[PDB]
Image 1 (cartoon, rainbow over the protein chains, first blue to last red):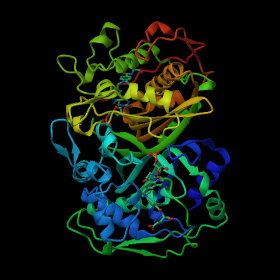
Image 2 (image 1 turned 30 degrees about the horizontal axis):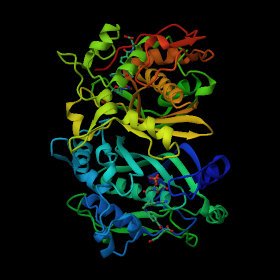
Image 3 (image 1 turned 45 degrees about the vertical axis):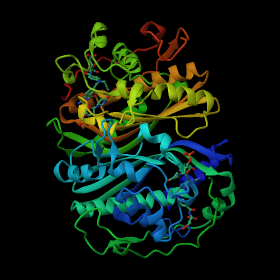
Length: 264
Length: 264
Ligand SMILES: C#CCN(Cc1ccc2[nH]c(N)nc(=O)c2c1)c1ccc(C(=O)N[C@@H](CCC(=O)O)C(=O)O)cc1
Ligand SMILES: C#CCN(Cc1ccc2[nH]c(N)nc(=O)c2c1)c1ccc(C(=O)N[C@@H](CCC(=O)O)C(=O)O)cc1
Ligand SMILES: *c1cc(=O)[nH]c(=O)n1[C@H]1C[C@H](O)[C@@H](COP(=O)(O)O)O1
Ligand SMILES: *c1cc(=O)[nH]c(=O)n1[C@H]1C[C@H](O)[C@@H](COP(=O)(O)O)O1
C-alpha cells in the first residue's frame, strides 16, 4: 500500500540504530500516523502476499477471550508458537483483556460487549474504548501488548477506529495488524448497522529489524496494486458468532510473498 | 502556536457536527497528530494568554498521587471544581492511576517510578508507558481520563513522549494538556540527565464546542509570537520533589486572553 511503503521508506531514511530486547538491532522512528478510508477498499498489502487465514483466526481467537494457542493449532495457525509455554498458554494477553478485564475486587469487565452496547445506545460517546494495556497483569503476559489501545468513533452513520500500537515491526507485524483491525471494524459495523469509515493507525516505536533489510528493499521496488474488497457472506446473531467461512476477499492480486525470520 | 492554530482550522474545515454528553454540541474530527520539538521553545500558546500557574500546580498534584482538590484550592486553582464531590474528591483519576494502579492480586503499581527506572536502566525498551485508562475503575471516576496513555522514547540522548488524548476540547483543554506534558518531559529529562526531544500529540475525538466558535475565529486572526523559554532552577533528588518556585518561564508575551465557558 502507498502509505505503508512510504512509512517503510521513512524508517530507512530517518531511523536511528537501536539495540533492542532481542539483540537483533533495529532502525526506528517514534510517532507516526496513517489513515485508511475503508470505503476505498480492504487495506491488505499487495506488494507481498499476506495470508488471511492467520489474520482471521487470530482475530476470532481474540474475540473468544482465548489465550491458549490450541484453537490456533486446530486451524493450522502457528504465529504464536514461539511465545507460548509448555502448555500452550500465552498468559492474560489480548483475548483475556478484551472479554474479561479483571477488576481489583474480583469482577470482570467485558470490553467488547460494552463497546457494542455503546455503539448501539450512545454512538456519540467519546469513551468507546478497548484497552489491552492492563498494567497489573503485564508481568504475567508472554509478550506485552503491541496493539494496546483502540477507540471507535461514529459520524454520519460511519464507524471509524483508531489504534495506538506501542511497538511495530514494520515488515512482519504491521501488515497483519492493519488487516486485523480493518476486519474488526467491518464486523462491528455489520453488527451495529453502520457503514465503514476510516482506520487510523498510530504507532509508537516503529521499526525495521536489521535482518529484514534485503526483504524491505525488495518490497520497495514493487508497485502497489488496487486494494481488494471484503465480503461478509453471512450476518451472525452476534459479533462472537463469526466463522472463518463467512469472509471472502475479491480482487486480491498481490506480488509474491517474501520470507523473513522473526525476532523472538 | 503554528501547529495548534492549524489544528483549529482543520476542525473547522473538515469537522462534523456531533451531539455530545454535555448537550452542548461539537464540531469534530477523529484522529490527528502533531509534533513539538521542545528544543525550539516551551510550547505554551501565545495567541491567547494562558495561566501557567494552574498548569504547574495540576501537574505536581498528579505526581503526588492526589485526587482531591484541597491542594489545588490552597493554591488558588479552581479548574477541577465542577466535577468534584461534596468532599472535593474526583475518584481514582490521573494521580491515583499514575502512582498506584491497583492490580487484581492486591498490589499497586507506581507507573511514574517504573518509567523513571526504565529510562535509567533500559531506555531502549519499547514498553515505557503510563496509562490512566483503568477499565476496572472507570465507574468510580468523576470524569474518564482525557489524556489517557503516554509513551516515552529515547534516541540520540534526547527524551521524547507521545500522548494519546482520547477526547480533546481544542479551545480550552488542549493548550493546558500540551504545556502540562511538555513540562513533564523536561522534569523527566532532568532527572535522567537527558536532553529534551519531541512531544508528539495524538488525538481521538478532537473537537470544538459549538459555544466556542466566536472565540476560535478571534484567536485564528492572530499571529503567533515567539515561543517562551523554560528554566528549571534546581535539580531535586526525585521527580516528586519539585516545587512551583523551581520553574521560570521567560520571554512570554501573549496576545490578550479570550474567555469561554466550560462544558460540564
Ligand atoms: C502482528 C501479528 C501477529 N504475529 C504475532 C507477533 C508476535 C511477536 C512478534 N515479534 C516480532 N519481532 N515481530 C512481530 O511482527 C511479531 C508478531 C505474527 C507472528 C508471526 C508472523 C509471521 O511469521 N508471518 C509470516 C507468515 C507465516 C505464516 O503464515 O504462518 C509472514 O511472512 O508474513 C506474523 C505475525
Ligand atoms: C486540560 C485541562 C485541565 N482542566 C480540567 C478539565 C476538566 C473538564 C473539561 N471539560 C471540558 N468540556 N473541557 C475541558 O477542556 C476540560 C478540562 C481545565 C479545566 C478548566 C479550564 C478552564 O476553565 N479554562 C480557563 C482557565 C481559568 C482558570 O484558570 O480558572 C481558561 O481560560 O483557560 C482549563 C483546564
Ligand atoms: C508485536 C505483536 C504485534 O501484534 N505487532 C508487532 O509489530 N509486534 C512486534 C513489535 C516488536 O517488534 C515485537 C514485540 O517486542 P517488544 O515488546 O516491543 O519488545 O513484536
Ligand atoms: C478532559 C480533561 C482534559 O485534561 N482535557 C480535555 O481536553 N478534556 C475534555 C474532553 C471533553 O471535551 C470533556 C470530557 O468529556 P468526555 O468524557 O469526553 O465526554 O473534557
